Image (cartoon, rainbow, N blue to C red; front, side, top):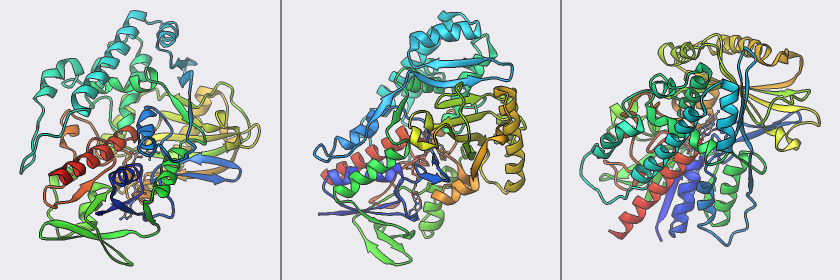
Length: 489
Ligand SMILES: Cc1cc2nc3c(=O)[nH]c(=O)nc-3n(C[C@H](O)[C@H](O)[C@H](O)COP(=O)(O)OP(=O)(O)OC[C@H]3O[C@@H](n4cnc5c(N)ncnc54)[C@H](O)[C@@H]3O)c2cc1C
């Protein structure tokens, strides 16, 4: 039986390992940290639990597909569907509580924004058709097509560009709404891959379909249960783990992978699958191999700055997912992507899992995950940025919720783009690999195979097909399909 080594226990690596296991490989995952899940990590601090990374759960069938590979194993993983997606607030007092029932969303949005129902209806149906077309056409495509060098392979993208909105920006399509608050609400979806609504293509209007047509869910135990259930499953089906052991080099011979090295020794495998960020994969682990320099130089997605606050009271106006919109979104993104700094009026996301699992906070308290969009680390003075952002975020919460939250903070943890970078070796602290700030960027990501080194594969959020849970999971599926194909040949 052949063996595979997976470099990193992120969601992509865990998924890949599970798939290779199902195929019959023996599998070992190396992890630099003393925990599994990478960005899907959690902490418990002074009476509060916090998810550290992903907070939004859509497309739960993609996780279930992994359990389905091992129908006999007993893994407790469940989730519920929510009636409400997000609460949205603005400085002028406007609040929109957004239903996951599309009929109710359209009616509510119509009244709250004084906007024609037909406009909202047509937009959501177009968002749906975009998703289904993109899924059918690009995410379900077969792997028949092969070759010795890199290729574009998407005349279909050009056929369908007018319908998908590939030649305009997200904001071009979102500016159809008359109320600018509604334009803003839908421009927010550019953050779902760390891009700007003013640059990312119009195909991204499909993103709200995920949470508004397909459901918004909450897993039992919070988001941490996603990586941990998968870790538990992996361990039960025989995947081996080497924790606190960073891979330092990927070994080859005669242009085929032979295994990896760590500070502790060398290990051989028939296959290597890296779940490490593609930049240090080349820069650090393949120092003797020629790097695809343009791929590695693609613009980096945005990062984040997060404050985790225990809060000594309740806010009945807040649900699980809440947004306090900046009064000037265009400036917000300009700072982030053009100047690598922070605008003074931020869009603040407040996530509160204690609304779903009351054990996540003391009785009558809340566990606030408080996040603003942020540039990656390019040498800024992060100490000053954090100090400044804190005061602006507190100012934002006074404008929108009419409370001085500083009187209620009982404990604080902070995560910056430096912390993000250190935690998981994500280059620049970018949350989603390369940004998607033009129509080529998706088609310019590193593939899941490697054209120089046979039997070396790549999985996760910095490579094809993209950042975020659903796409990282597809990364692993595609990687495993490739390998099975190669076996058959
Ligand atoms: C704050 C935040 C919020 C987010 N929210 C969302 C969300 O709501 N929805 C969403 O879809 N996505 C979200 N994301 C993004 C999402 O978390 C990632 O894109 C995705 O989970 C990353 O998966 P991955 O497979 O790339 O693995 P990663 O999570 O990046 O982890 C990779 C693993 O590899 C390990 N590793 C690296 N180098 C080595 C080495 N040399 N040796 C051994 N091990 C190594 C790392 O330590 C890490 O454990 C969020 C990200 C952040 C930071």
